[PDB]
Image 1 (tube, rainbow, N blue to C red):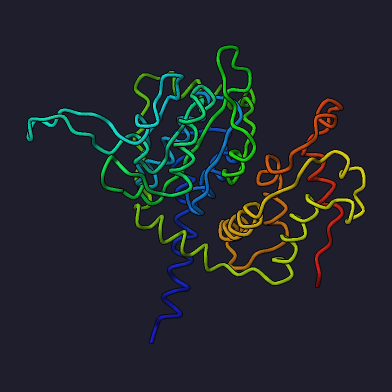
Image 2 (cartoon, rainbow, N blue to C red):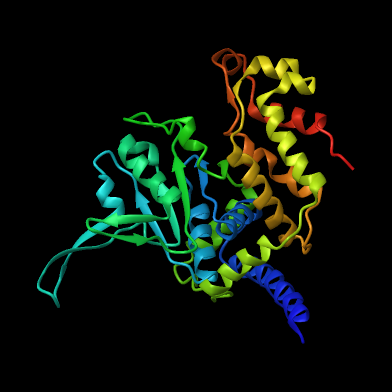
Length: 330
């Protein structure tokens, strides 16, 4: 037989395709390796991402370009105060063939969904979005339809919204795999973006490097990456250090933290560590795979008390301290 050799070849094939996807995205996008890597981890692991800040031209062009290179549909939904939960789920059209008014699958039926300024809509609309993320299906009136596979929600919140704003509470932000704080590009990158995009004949058509089916195969390949018992227990210890920090010798952190990270943090750390391993051409996880993504997975899952926030304490400093303190069992 040849089943083990074929499995080896399929894994190297898909590891090389990820390199080809990044290269193709780079023909349109500049100075954004970090964002693209996280978007890729998201779509391949099934996780959703929350961004703090509204993404500018270079970031939204990065999302639409990545989608094109991966044969995935992309829809941007502008969240507004008058948006209804039913506006997300269905769209009223006039079908000319049937000659009547019927509700077709709404904007959430896509692969990449940029949910822009989710804090501009009422909590019921936010709940509707999170229900889609959690249940992966919705009922258009009578019959239930599953959402597409893969499905990534990239939700953005504007932190300095001077008009009406309903920011997501922490039980809700815990449904996102990562929270990422957006920053401006450096001047050299911004110069190159301006150069490319200002050209009115700039070619934005990228080639499809992988099919939608290949994306689902890449997820299955990542799922096969191995993680030792030692590293599995390490993930659990990191999570428990956020809940009972005084028991790890972090008495100060116990004073800053109201409550720690849910079980979702452990699951994301595991799946994301495997994706990082796969993206670094390995089929086993290393401790550096876990440490590289700990802040992105944990920053929004550690809730600080009112007094710690006023004093200027950041979950970043807390996560760094935990990473310096928790040991791995050989």
